[PDB]
Image (tube, rainbow, N blue to C red):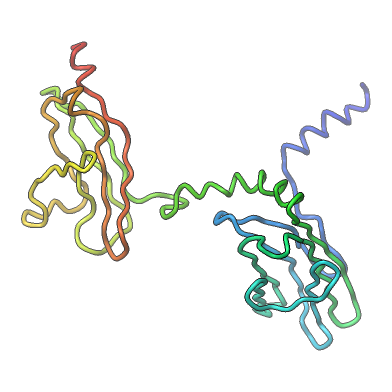
Length: 231
């Protein structure tokens, strides 16, 4: 139609322009289930003078910072950070932050109760990506193989941000490809020679990281012998 309203309704939907739930203050107090998959309350609050009060309310009651609800405000204008690490209350979940600075006052409520949270949890899914249990956003070392002229796969990973001893170490499902470790350095990126591979030796070439923490192995499934056969 001439209105083309819906069409723009899509375009604006594409922009994904958020940041609206404010008040006389500057609340953006919404519910962000973090990457770690936890609960997050966050409004802004540009003014912490005298009266300047924020009221943590849960289930129609005013609560306080402590173990179950942790709050952290660094009064740089009054940014309100607040966390919750799960549900485990009496399954209930509803928080109203009413803030006022000086003479102004604003309300902001969040809800995550069993029936409700499960809803936000889907959205959390995007963040729920807890598979990482370590690397998180942006990895450090990565594999990469290349069948060289001799038809061998030249296994090589690539190192990043790390200062302990060496970087990685090639493996193969508990099988340690035992090469000279720290005697001849092998520092930086490491390259080996899969001089022919076999469908009974193939699988995945493991990269292992042990440093000032525990470990860290991440690898893909390598098959070359199946291709060699085609050569």
